[PDB]
C-alpha cells in the first residue's frame, strides 16, 4: 500500500447512450392543409323580383 | 458515512489533501462513474477496475 505514482494513460474510453434513429429520417408527416372554401351545392335564386 | 475517504500527499516542502466528500469533492464523481482499463495487448483483455 505504498501508493506510488503510475505512468501516464494511453487513451480514453467514453461510454454514453446513443439515440435511436430508426424512427426519424422517415418522410415528414405535416399537418394536412385545410381545404379552400368551396361553393355549397344547391344554391338557387330564392329572390324573385316583385311584380 | 462509509465511502468517504481522504487522500494525503507529503512532498519535501509542502503537503496536499483531498476529500471524497463535502466541499472540495468533484461533481464528476457523482454525475459520472470512472473506471480504469488495464489492457493486455497480447490477450486483448480489458480488465476494468473501478476508479475514484
Image (cartoon, helix red, strand yellow):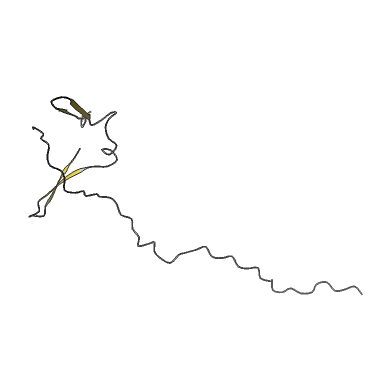
Q: Residue most toward the front? A: B13
Task: Pick whichever, A44 or B29, lies toward us.
Answer: B29
Q: How many marks?
A: 0
Looking at the image, which residue is at 56% across and 65% down?
A33
Quarter holding residue B6: top left
Task: Pick whichever, B5 or B14, lies toward us.
Answer: B14
Q: Is A27 situated left or right of B21 in this image?
A: right
Q: Is A12 situated left or right of A18 in this image?
A: left
Q: Residue most toward the right? A: A51
Q: Quadrant of the C terminus of chain B?
A: top left
Q: Is residue B39 above or below residue A20?
A: above
Looking at the image, which residue is at 45% across and 65% down?
A28
Quarter holding residue A36: bottom right
Q: Quadrant of the N terminus of chain B?
A: top left
Q: Is residue A49 above or below residue B17?
A: below
Task: Pick whichever, B23 or A26, lies toward us.
Answer: B23
Looking at the image, which residue is at 27% across and 35% down?
B26
Residue A6: percent from left, percent from top? 12, 39
Quarter holding residue A37: bottom right
Residue B25: percent from left, percent from top? 26, 32
Residue A5: percent from left, percent from top? 12, 37
Q: Is B25 situated left or right of A8 in this image?
A: right
Looking at the image, which residue is at 27% across and 30% down?
B24
Q: Is residue B43 above or below residue A5?
A: below
Amino acid at each position: 500500500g505504498g501508493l506510488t505514482c503510475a505512468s501516464a494513460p494511453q487513451g480514453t474510453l467514453r461510454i454514453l447512450e446513443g439515440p435511436q434513429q430508426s424512427l426519424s429520417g422517415s418522410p415528414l408527416q405535416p399537418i394536412p392543409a385545410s381545404p379552400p372554401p368551396q361553393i355549397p351545392p344547391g344554391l338557387r335564386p330564392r329572390f324573385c323580383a316583385f311584380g | 458515512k462509509r465511502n468517504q475517504r481522504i487522500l494525503a500527499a507529503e512532498t519535501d516542502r509542502l503537503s496536499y489533501v483531498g476529500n471524497n466528500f463535502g466541499t472540495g469533492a468533484l461533481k464528476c464523481n457523482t454525475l459520472c462513474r470512472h473506471f480504469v482499463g488495464i489492457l493486455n495487448k497480447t490477450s486483448g483483455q480489458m480488465e476494468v477496475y473501478d476508479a475514484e
